[PDB]
Image (spheres, rainbow, N blue to C red):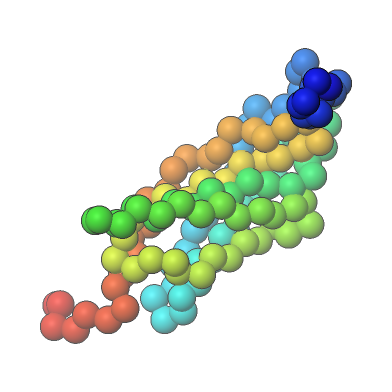
Amino acid sequence: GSSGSSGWILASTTEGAPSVAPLNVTVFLNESSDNVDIRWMKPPTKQQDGELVGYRISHVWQSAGISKELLEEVGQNGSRARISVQVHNATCTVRIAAVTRGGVGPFSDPVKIFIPAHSGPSSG
């Protein structure tokens, strides 16, 4: 390393990844509680592919004039995730994916959840 001593492209894989997403993908938004319930199912990934070590949840918050992005990290031993409302009155898109000892599979269908403002009476 000539005045660099940078990383070193170590052994890399050539194939092997969960080309599938989690099932029973459901996302509940509590109006009384500033938390988001997330429950999914384990994929059929049981073939030569390998095994599941964890999942990948990506929830981004998009609001008028304010756009934030969040990323949760959950392992195999969980089958459950929760997120503390980071933004109100904004459209957040939830997405979960299967993670293995090889890589990260494709995220499931995008779920657009409507985050109701703190409080707003005289609505209906």
